[PDB]
Amino acid sequence: VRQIAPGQTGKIADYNYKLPDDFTGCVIAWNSNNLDSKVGGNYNYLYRL
Amino acid sequence: GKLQDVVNQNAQALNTLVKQLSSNFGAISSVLNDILSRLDPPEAEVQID
Image (cartoon, rainbow over all chains, first blue to last red; front, side, top):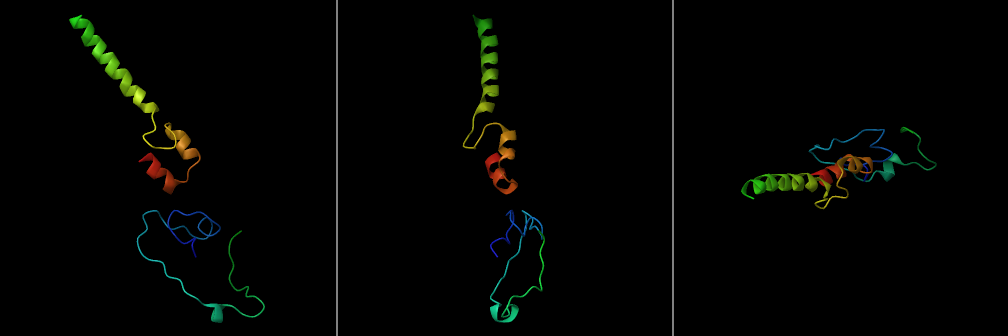
């Protein structure tokens, strides 16, 4: 979640989507363990390598 | 001497203007190109500024 900020560099901002340096707005995140996590491991969401 | 000072107060005041290009003013390096080599954009701008 730390990776979502303007000007950063990492496995998401480099290849998934980049926030512009002049970006204005807000970022919101919250807990979804009970819904998006299942016993055994969820492979539903991909990312780039 | 009166004319010799006119020439000497110009060349001396001109050399120091060029000589000011080799100072840092607080930046990591005086030369601009080496700043871009080992710095990402969003942190190099504050050094360039």
